[PDB]
Length: 20
Image (cartoon, rainbow, N blue to C red):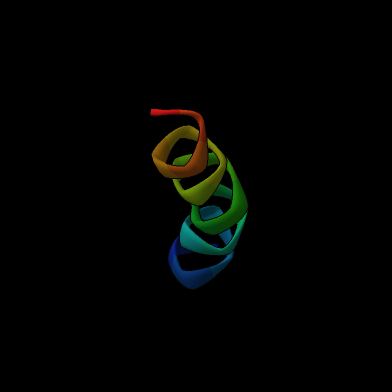
């Protein structure tokens, strides 16, 4: 679950990174 939750955060955080 934790690595999976982090697997969900991965794209979102990088999406933000790309957005910023």
